[PDB]
Length: 239
Length: 241
Ligand SMILES: C[S@@+](CC[C@H](N)C(=O)[O-])C[C@H]1O[C@@H](n2cnc3c(N)ncnc32)[C@H](O)[C@@H]1O
Ligand SMILES: C[S@@+](CC[C@H](N)C(=O)[O-])C[C@H]1O[C@@H](n2cnc3c(N)ncnc32)[C@H](O)[C@@H]1O
Ligand SMILES: [Cl-]
Ligand SMILES: [Cl-]
Ligand SMILES: [Cl-]
Image (tube, rainbow over all chains, first blue to last red; front, side, top):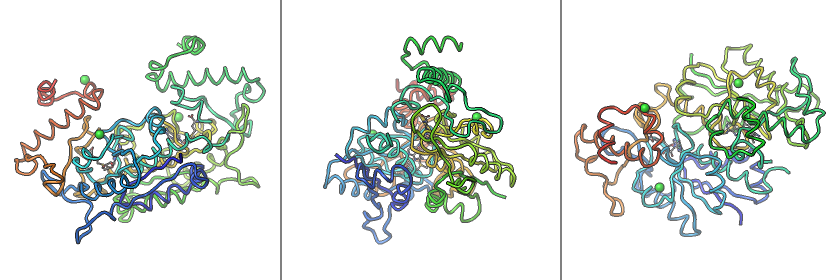
């Protein structure tokens, strides 16, 4: 089935503008997935059409009200089943494994907070899970939503050109360096093996550089990786 | 004099459109910072305006060419000193500590790749550092750039008003934050915790700190381990597990 990603946000047009750029917009154009911005302001009923108000506990910090977010999610669910993700720093830290897990859903609803956060009762009532884009804080869930959609949708066969099979994190490693023309640029030659080597020599050089980069930059990934005999010998030879 | 973030990208209009929205767009309006999309295609010099080409090593996977990126960065540097960040999965995993460190700079240039990545020679020549938005891969550096800018620019005093305080929030404190609530006091039979409605400032502080430690313990025990817990935090933790 076509993968669908609903984004509940006070800035739906931001979501539409973002997805008219790049390889992903072509996948939308041909129907491999679809992004569905939902205007949270459409689910207000008060005279001031209110989606945020002063929180409880003191001060004037703003928190997203529960009723509009509840109504927006219930509206989606009334038409078609969906998997509800609240974007929240308290959630699961988003990694390539998360993206592979979310890939299995055909219909995901992302709820975007603003200001101090989202009233936690509607999260308790409606969320299937919480996901954090990383160990940092941004002003809204919008950027976290589109980033996740990007990471998940690009795994749909046919979205990228004929590869996401050997890239960083997918392999449990950081990828080798890449180069293109010209062969010489400001005194730096492209490694000769990539110009004139055979397949196995290029594979060996890339695997070596990949392990090197991972050991130097992300030793924690090395510890988590189940190494092939060949990868382990290379790792030993750099230590 | 304000903070400036330049974004080298083949999609400058995407960057422009993103910062029309939300609290950051008001910060730009009153001149607390500025975002400058830099059109990488303006720095090609060949007849096909080429920013990417087939990589070396076999196949037709595309890699961003070194010359336009080099020319783009040297142009900025000829105008003003700037700190050059290559967006790349191999870089430092972006955290709140990273955002706090980058806040120090008054001018930051982000280099956005596409396709298989960026020719690593221009990275080696021009990058002051590489940063990864996280342990996953996206189609382009654009989203990583604007996300980092968001996390950094929101720390500029005055960008956020009374609507949110960045001094006490997730990760900044080493913890995950407590739950929040707003009107109405009762929603579908679920009541806002009474302490937030009628407790005093100290009672609210105690409850919030407890829920924060509980949430961090349940969701991110790794964060508990690396935080130097205060005497009070230590005891709350013990009075749980
Ligand atoms: C400024 S944040 C509120 C964060 C909250 N005060 C805290 O410290 O945990 C406003 C909105 O941005 C989104 N957001 C901010 N950081 C996020 C992150 N790391 N992961 C997912 N969403 C995030 C969330 O949807 C959140 O409701
Ligand atoms: C599809 S990625 C290529 C990544 C490379 N093939 C690898 O496996 O490491 C294309 C561009 O998106 C950006 N990008 C992808 N993932 C990123 C991340 N985790 N952090 C920062 N930038 C990222 C980079 O600028 C990169 O040049
Ligand atoms: Cl949850
Ligand atoms: Cl570097
Ligand atoms: Cl410690």
